[PDB]
Length: 289
Length: 314
Image 1: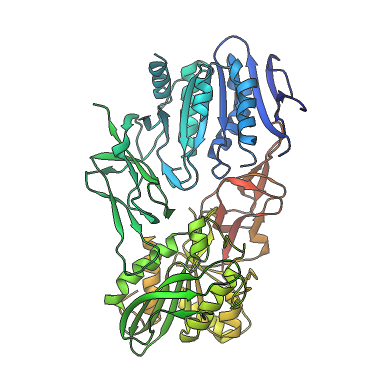
Image 2: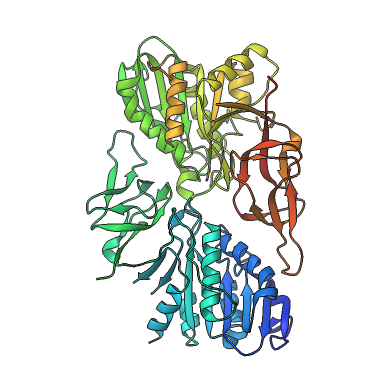
């Protein structure tokens, strides 16, 4: 009964506004929102914090909120740094974003997190508009642009362009790499002045387009303690040990090797942890044919 | 009913593998914790434990490496290893026991008719503790923390015991040996150290491994259990334990091993309910080294976010 979702300020108000997106009743959640409305030009929504466990997205989004008042040349940029603050309520949060934010933007940039248990390459993932989405994605000049075969559905259910930058909690994340990349996308979109620059990653200034399919998505054959045996960006040969699975019911039993099925690059890899059978423990990727 | 017991004989010469059976109780069925024992006759006795907490797997992994290496490397004595003392926690991805909510370490020596954590503690205390003089715990500092590969030594009033334990700890040759009177000694510490007068060594694993391997090998050499040829000593006091003044998103601004000056920003706190409000700086109270620091995460007011340390007086 009581109230629909609402914003605490008017999005048509020129300049900078800060307020909340109130999601109706657990009780009401008030998600802080930043909006800079500088008229005609590109309209972009930036979201972060799907995983309350890994906050590099939210930190990058807050930095952007402080910087955009001086740098934003035109258009409209809405920033919701933390989408899952408590992290049904998840349906109602999705609904609030769909009703109040998605209608006003043409593009959505999700600062998506895999969680603290994965390491992954600083990158953009993509699953006509595909050509547009892929060119815009490459314009970020991140170390990897991945063609990988739900929030993209919401965004697609309004026919908007969806860009997904991937964050993980492992050693490979690189916050300044992601900053440089997001700035390159805002430059590419025409929202801020400047020239795109590849950030230095692993002592290099390069971008690479890779693809991943089912054979490259390595899964555990059975339950146990997964131990990674490679790092993000490692070039592996077919048959190389990507990780080892240790059994928990016995210290005499053998461990199981988890091997790469083809020559490929380690895009993401799980940290050491207990996994069930058929759980993905490494994402490999290869260059396009 | 059933008492806790081992499924094999510790006095069996050579390498044995089996289980420690924790009987059924009021909250769950019996548990079988795998145990390794390498008996090479007369010499030092040692228990090595991992997996007291469930979100730390480097200890369990290191323990399993020792299980495979000690059959050829152990020269004498007896080494018992339990790579995961809290399988319930390891499997639930939880810090403490998911059934009873208890931190297995703080409940030692437990009780046979208590909750699951208490029965696990009772089983270890009745069957493993009485046969060892030294316990090595491969301890989870916290997966939300990055900390130096180290041993944290808690000051105690018994001078010889403190001297012996600190010397053995330093002989591991890890990056840091940290003197710290944290008073988080309920359970296992009080049991082994104060009640039993034993050598208790805690190696620290944060959530941020060949260092640890080499360290534990040096430790084993120093204990006379493995033959071979095998570092900063720092202290942390209350002014070195930095806390958030209010709830928000903590953002670290320094890394483990960084040497910070008095007044340097160690981290920043971003307020949770506002994008207009300014962030709060969390500063070092003295020139010190970063021993441990939290990962970017949500914190409540007065939560510890960084542990700084200073070199011990020479």
